[PDB]
Amino acid sequence: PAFRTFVASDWGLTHLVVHEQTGEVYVGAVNRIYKLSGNLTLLRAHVTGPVEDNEKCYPPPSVQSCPHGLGSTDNVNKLLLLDYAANRLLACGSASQGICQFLRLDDLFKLGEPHHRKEHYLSSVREAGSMAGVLIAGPPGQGQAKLFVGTPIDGKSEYFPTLSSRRLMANEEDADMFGFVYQDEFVSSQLKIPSDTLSKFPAFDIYYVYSFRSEQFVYYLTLQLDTQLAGEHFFTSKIVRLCVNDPKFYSYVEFPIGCEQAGVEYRLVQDAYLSRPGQALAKQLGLAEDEEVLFTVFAQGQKNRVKPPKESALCLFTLRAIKEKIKERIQSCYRGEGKLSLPWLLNKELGCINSPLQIDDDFCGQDFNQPLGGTVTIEGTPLFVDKEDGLTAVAAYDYQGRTVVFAGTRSGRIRKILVDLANPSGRPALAYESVVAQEGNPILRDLVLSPNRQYLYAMTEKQVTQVPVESCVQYTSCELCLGSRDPHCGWCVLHSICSRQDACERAEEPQRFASDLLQCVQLTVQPRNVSVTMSQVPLVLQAWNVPDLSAGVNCSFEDFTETESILEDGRIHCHSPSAREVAPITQGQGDQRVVKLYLKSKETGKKFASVDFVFYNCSVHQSCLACVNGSFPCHWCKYRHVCTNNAADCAFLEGRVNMSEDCPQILPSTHIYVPVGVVKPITLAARNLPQPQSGQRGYECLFHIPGSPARVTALRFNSSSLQCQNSSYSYEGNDVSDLPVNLSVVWNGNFVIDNPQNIQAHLYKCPALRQSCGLCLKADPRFECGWCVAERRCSLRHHCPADSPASWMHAHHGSSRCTDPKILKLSPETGPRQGGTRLTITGENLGLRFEDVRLGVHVGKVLCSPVESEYISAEQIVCEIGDASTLRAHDALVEVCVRDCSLHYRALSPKRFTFVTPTFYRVSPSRGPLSGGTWIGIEGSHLNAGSDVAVSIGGRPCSFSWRNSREIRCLTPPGHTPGSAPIVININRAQLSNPEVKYNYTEDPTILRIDPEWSINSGGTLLTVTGTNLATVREPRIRAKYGGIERENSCMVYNDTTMVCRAPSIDNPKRSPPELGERPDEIGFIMDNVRTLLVLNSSSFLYYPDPVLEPLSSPLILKGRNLLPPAPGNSRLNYTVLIGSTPCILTVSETQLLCEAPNKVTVRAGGFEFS
Ligand SMILES: *[C@@H]1O[C@H](CO)[C@@H](O[C@@H]2O[C@H](CO)[C@@H](O[C@@H]3O[C@H](CO[C@H]4O[C@H](CO)[C@@H](O)[C@H](O[C@H]5O[C@H](CO)[C@@H](O)[C@H](O)[C@@H]5O)[C@@H]4O)[C@@H](O)[C@H](O[C@H]4O[C@H](CO)[C@@H](O)[C@H](O)[C@@H]4O)[C@@H]3O)[C@H](O)[C@H]2NC(C)=O)[C@H](O)[C@H]1NC(C)=O
Ligand SMILES: *[C@H]1O[C@H](CO)[C@@H](O[C@@H]2O[C@H](CO)[C@@H](O[C@@H]3O[C@H](CO[C@H]4O[C@H](CO)[C@@H](O)[C@H](O[C@H]5O[C@H](CO)[C@@H](O)[C@H](O)[C@@H]5O)[C@@H]4O)[C@@H](O)[C@H](O[C@H]4O[C@H](CO)[C@@H](O)[C@H](O)[C@@H]4O)[C@@H]3O)[C@H](O)[C@H]2NC(C)=O)[C@H](O)[C@H]1NC(C)=O
Ligand SMILES: *[C@@H]1O[C@H](CO)[C@@H](O[C@@H]2O[C@H](CO)[C@@H](O[C@@H]3O[C@H](CO[C@H]4O[C@H](CO)[C@@H](O)[C@H](O)[C@@H]4O)[C@@H](O)[C@H](O[C@H]4O[C@H](CO)[C@@H](O)[C@H](O)[C@@H]4O)[C@@H]3O)[C@H](O)[C@H]2NC(C)=O)[C@H](O)[C@H]1NC(C)=O
Ligand SMILES: *[C@@H]1O[C@H](CO)[C@@H](O[C@@H]2O[C@H](CO)[C@@H](O[C@@H]3O[C@H](CO[C@H]4O[C@H](CO)[C@@H](O)[C@H](O[C@H]5O[C@H](CO)[C@@H](O)[C@H](O)[C@@H]5O)[C@@H]4O)[C@@H](O)[C@H](O)[C@@H]3O)[C@H](O)[C@H]2NC(C)=O)[C@H](O)[C@H]1NC(C)=O
Ligand SMILES: *[C@@H]1O[C@H](CO)[C@@H](O[C@@H]2O[C@H](CO)[C@@H](O[C@@H]3O[C@H](CO)[C@@H](O)[C@H](O[C@H]4O[C@H](CO)[C@@H](O)[C@H](O)[C@@H]4O)[C@@H]3O)[C@H](O)[C@H]2NC(C)=O)[C@H](O)[C@H]1NC(C)=O
Ligand SMILES: *[C@@H]1O[C@H](CO)[C@@H](O[C@@H]2O[C@H](CO)[C@@H](O[C@@H]3O[C@H](CO)[C@@H](O)[C@H](O[C@H]4O[C@H](CO)[C@@H](O)[C@H](O)[C@@H]4O)[C@@H]3O)[C@H](O)[C@H]2NC(C)=O)[C@H](O)[C@H]1NC(C)=O
Ligand SMILES: *[C@@H]1O[C@H](CO)[C@@H](O[C@@H]2O[C@H](CO)[C@@H](O[C@@H]3O[C@H](CO)[C@@H](O)[C@H](O)[C@@H]3O)[C@H](O)[C@H]2NC(C)=O)[C@H](O)[C@H]1NC(C)=O
Ligand SMILES: *[C@@H]1O[C@H](CO)[C@@H](O[C@@H]2O[C@H](CO)[C@@H](O)[C@H](O)[C@H]2NC(C)=O)[C@H](O)[C@H]1NC(C)=O
Ligand SMILES: *[C@@H]1O[C@H](CO)[C@@H](O)[C@H](O)[C@H]1NC(C)=O
Ligand SMILES: *[C@@H]1O[C@H](CO)[C@@H](O)[C@H](O)[C@H]1NC(C)=O
């Protein structure tokens, strides 16, 4: 569905109201007043707006000339009131000292607009909604129609009354309009602001928010100023009341109003709405039918009426309770107690006069003790509190007793609240939230339910929106319908839809309509699971919370089939579809198809109740495991090798599989080892292997080798063992020694027995991977594969001739020395004399255990201790070299003795290991900031030696980058205290020092001045920067943060104090700098780890928008915008206008460039160029 809507094409909207007969919607706006249909189509548009005028002018230009300058200004609709009696609309504007309009009801024809007399003027105030009031009428000939109206005054105390009682004549042209009900030279039916109270408190004013007629009175919810709370402005939200029949204005009352939530004050009215409570809230709030109630909205505190806080609270007042607070206060002043206490009205406090009277609710005020205030602030019952999104508006209504509340939000959202304090629940609960102007257009106070009370017109700054009170049809399921709780919604069982009682046909009958989730349609089928192969199966259906279906019912499995059913007891009996019908469904979905079996009612003809119904298919299972150990009742036939539901369809009795453990499967043994090109049998074990029956062949082993697949026939010895016959196998590659191969055991040609563990045959080759004795004895003792001296190759005893009783050698337990060790290459080629180096030797024919190579390794004379974990047997030794300080040699060859330094069992390295002692002499900055982060370049000799390197400045470690013969480059850590620091480099067990080469911690560079204090949006101009220690940073750069973007640019250092920098581009398509200029969010410099320089607090650097220049003996004149910026001091751009290469002498002006020419033209200023 879509929300019916009226969009405000050009201007903001201010007020909305609904005609109780028609449902036409009238809409007050700035410069416009619209008539709209119930579904928000435009019906008529009145122009009321842009008027040539001025607020300062009294009587507006129409009546008298004003010396103040006039301008086309907007006319804001301040007020809107339906006068049904005189078939019209009072449409009160502003911007003419507040003259009022009369528009005819059905066409908006201006009937009248009185503006001659002073009463025809209402207020200068140009603010929308700060005004309110009520229209009240009697029959024609009797006491005529009156308007009670409050407005702000703006300090124009003597021009306008804030509250007034005014006359509404039947002729709109009649001059008597908006005249006071009773005017006297002593007392008029109006209430003015006293001049003395405006002198004392400068801009006190009364803003009228909401207003309503009740029984015989007229109430107003108001906002006022600090008068006992010159200083600052703080507001107090109050209730006002008058008797309708009090021309003298003596009935005026004024009590402060608000409410508190866990010690948090809410004292600013944003809206209100008088309503009924209906049977529900009335009863447990203790009220009579026609007793009224007032829903309200307050913001937190007493601050900023112009822009209130998010924190907002919906409170409640029963009018009987406000009536009692007023009666209680009057029966109190008529006891003579205290003062009247009304600051803004009576500055000097007059006292309460005692008198004997019958104080009633009918009391309409008397001559003495006059207009009076209120001491005890009236507290309201809180209901719902929003903390992240401020309430703005409210309405409410009676629905079948339960009291529904509507609440606008700053976001453009409406809340639908059941108030349940008087209802059973713990506290009043939100039911639902809805969207109007999602982008964040706030909802306005004027929020009216339609006449039929089916919709709720919700107004924003920019759009009216028809939001339905009931729209239960968005609810798809009984479970969600009654789950939303918004009380209009019930499940109309047989129509399977969610809607109100009056909308569900026959709802009054038993079980036809559901209102509590427990009434939900609940359905079950006895034979939940039915096989594809079955047909017309009898099923029984149990359903609860369903009306009398003696009308008739059909079963529809989905929109595929439909079978007739008959009714007995509390059960429904229908049949499954035919095999002819069932399979059209199940085709494609294979294993099973869960299908939603519905009930189609004969009365409605709509599916309402559902169940999970399963269509299972046994035959499509193509293995025992899937068949039995699946999820369903399926039987496997060992012998036919087919899955089916029927026991009898099996071959015969003793071939039925019902249990998963009884399935034909191959069991594992310890791994199947198969050498290539060797005649071997492969015995297998298994379980429940079938005796092949009539017309059935025997067993075979099929090997799935990509190169060659072998078919070898086998013998089944019993139900538990197999064996493929003597054969040899191969694969073409010689690429991988150990190849695992999928094998399938077949019988009768194509029946493959199940292989759960997925047992494989490993085809291994006596080595196509190992041409070294050490590699063979390295591999599995299982393979039986071993090294054969004479051949110079490696194969089994089987494949190698015994010319000697010990000609074939196998690693017995690894106690097998292996001949002629050889070293290929070793890493680190160089090392420190001190030792500690990890030598990484890689050979081919080494020892097979660690404890023989340990003690064997030596570097010339120097004892080398080998490492266990890092040793890879007969391929690689990792060894730690000892102290070589005492060695005379500079370089020595590496030696391994396998176990004993025997003459055949020794290896010597092809090239030799070199000992050096690295030294360093210079550092390439010798200075750097205390924070660190400096790129250091240590120069020396032999710096690339050994394994590990660690550089320590002041004991603290340097972050290493890269190493060289001649250089070590690392990044400096933070220094503790500024000044000279030791540089310690340790390579393995060698720790080299130099006290002549030190590092000097500085002092951190500083930034003092940037000279020009500005640049343009694209940047690129020269900046003459000054500071200290600038030569100690090799690559400094400028940083600037504009908006959400951060950008950087380069610098060129000259002195320790001077630097030229190219200004950073801030080019943002989101924000452009103004003509006036703008500071960046951040500005600074990136200098290593000195982070205090990244953000400059004191900087006044400005960014102007991207010079503008216009193209095509007398001098050159070049015109354009943005040539000169509004910069502090003298400082301006050094412009140079050039011709091919020759610069000119020019005088620069704000719009023009005065170059001088003797008769390709380029203009330069910093990093800027244009032709
Ligand atoms: C429950 O589930 C079962 C199994 O999943 C469904 O039964 C299948 O029905 C469909 C028909 O729509 C079959 O698919 C078609 O197969 C034919 C050729 O089938 C041949 O190959 C089979 C596969 O090995 C083999 O089983 C067949 O032998 C059977 O039939 C004989 C005689 O009745 C019987 O004695 C045997 O015991 C077997 O039962 C047969 O040799 C093929 O023409 C189709 O392929 C074409 O279309 C596809 C898709 O467009 C396309 O990709 C191809 O290129 C080709 O053009 C098609 O695949 C399927 O074979 C049946 N399954 C089995 C095991 O037989 C069935 O939906 C459900 N059962 C019921 C009762 O509803
Ligand atoms: C290290 O190197 C840096 C930059 O490389 C040096 O900074 C500059 O030094 C030179 C001298 O070596 C100075 O140039 C001289 O300027 C004067 C006239 O100054 C006027 O013109 C300037 C250039 O347009 C302008 O910036 C000046 O504005 C400054 O002063 C105002 C007001 O006091 C101040 O508010 C600003 O902040 C500016 O700082 C000013 O209007 C000129 O007379 C010199 O000419 C002489 O020298 C040349 C060459 O030797 C010779 O040929 C002539 O005959 C003549 O005798 C010269 O052009 C420049 O002022 C320095 N820049 C700054 C920003 O101060 C820096 O001095 C070196 N540092 C160290 C520690 O050694
Ligand atoms: C289903 O059918 C399967 C397969 O047909 C049977 O499995 C066989 O079980 C028997 C036990 O009866 C196993 O027989 C044993 O074989 C050993 C032979 O290994 C040697 O083979 C060759 C040639 O002799 C040598 O070169 C090689 O070096 C091996 O050493 C014998 O050593 C065993 O004999 C020992 O046990 C018996 C009985 O206790 C004693 O009498 C002997 O003195 C001796 O101690 C033994 O005979 C045979 O390996 C299995 N077959 C296969 C093919 O592997 C199942 O028994 C049967 N299952 C059921 C439930 O009925
Ligand atoms: C497929 O659909 C069928 C619909 O028929 C579902 O079957 C029902 O499954 C549930 C459990 O999953 C059973 O509920 C249990 O009942 C137990 C008591 O069982 C006895 O009483 C049964 C009814 O009175 C009776 O059917 C049953 O006899 C069965 O066993 C006999 C011996 O094996 C066999 O010969 C008969 O044919 C028959 O099948 C017992 O005497 C109780 O102890 C449990 O706590 C539980 O409540 C239903 O009884 C099943 N209904 C039937 C008619 O058997 C089935 O769930 C669906 N399959 C899947 C996978 O979802
Ligand atoms: C102005 O607003 C009015 C209402 O304020 C509105 O006119 C109404 O439209 C509704 C439908 O939106 C109509 O209600 C129909 O009543 C007839 C019986 O006479 C039914 O046959 C209709 O049922 C149909 O629609 C159902 C729901 O979509 C279907 O389930 C069903 O199969 C039928 O097709 C329906 O209930 C109604 O005619 C008027 N209301 C009145 C009082 O006449 C309209 O949307 C707005 N018009 C304009 C010009 O802006
Ligand atoms: C509840 O269930 C009952 C019984 O299960 C079911 O009755 C069905 O009624 C339809 C008529 O609506 C029957 O279909 C007819 O059968 C004749 C042959 O005898 C066909 O030639 C007709 O089919 C034509 O029309 C179809 C629909 O327009 C087309 O799809 C088709 O191409 C043909 O032109 C005709 O429809 C049907 O035989 C019975 N069902 C059975 C199982 O016999 C009924 O739907 C349900 N009852 C109610 C009141 O809804
Ligand atoms: C040797 O056998 C192995 C294992 O049987 C084969 O590898 C894998 O085979 C399995 C079948 O069990 C495949 O798994 C499948 O996964 C999908 C997941 O979407 C699932 O839907 C299927 O039901 C099935 O279980 C798997 O794809 C396959 N592996 C690869 C990488 O394809 C292997 O194919 C055999 N080797 C050769 C050379 O054929
Ligand atoms: C066959 O069914 C068995 C028994 O139900 C399944 O056994 C599972 O085995 C794993 C071990 O791999 C256990 O951790 C699970 O707890 C077992 N599951 C259950 C439910 O008992 C097995 O998954 C099924 N196998 C196949 C191939 O379908
Ligand atoms: C072949 O297998 C048979 C039976 O297992 C056995 O007697 C014979 O030793 C095997 N022959 C060869 C050459 O391996
Ligand atoms: C270290 O640097 C500081 C600040 O630049 C300097 O004053 C001091 O002389 C330097 N120390 C040495 C030993 O040169």
Image (spheres, rainbow, N blue to C red):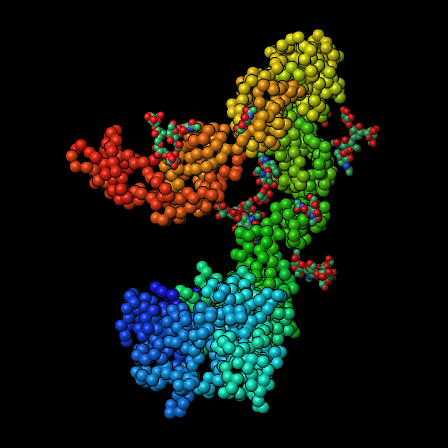
Seen in the picture, residue 337 relative to 49 is either above or below; the reply is below
Residue 949 horizontal/vertical position (percent) = 61, 23
Q: Quadrant of the N terminus?
A: bottom left
Q: Quadrant of ligand 9?
A: top right
Residue at (40, 91) in percent of width and height: 142
Residue 635 horizontal/vertical position (percent) = 67, 51
Residue at (28, 72) in percent of width and height: 61
Seen in the picture, residue 971 relative to 172 is either above or below; the reply is above
Q: Is residue 1140 left or right of residue 502?
A: left
Question: Which residue is outermost to the bottom?
Answer: 141
Q: Is residue 156 visible?
A: yes
- How many numbered marks does the figure carry? 0
Q: Is residue 489 left or right of residue 784?
A: left
Of the pair 879 and 524, the residue shown nearer to us: 879
Residue at (53, 84) in percent of width and height: 369
Residue 209 horizontal/vertical position (percent) = 46, 72
Q: Quadrant of the C terminus?
A: top left
Where, by quadrant of the figure, is residue 1018 drawn?
Answer: top left
Residue at (65, 50) in percent of width and height: 630
Seen in the picture, residue 144 relative to 777 is either above or below; the reply is below
Where, by quadrant of the figure, is residue 104 drawn?
Answer: bottom left
Residue 287 horizontal/vertical position (percent) = 59, 82
Seen in the picture, residue 1127 relative to 198 is either above or below; the reply is above
Q: Is residue 824 visible?
A: no
Of the pair 251 and 500, the residue shown nearer to us: 251
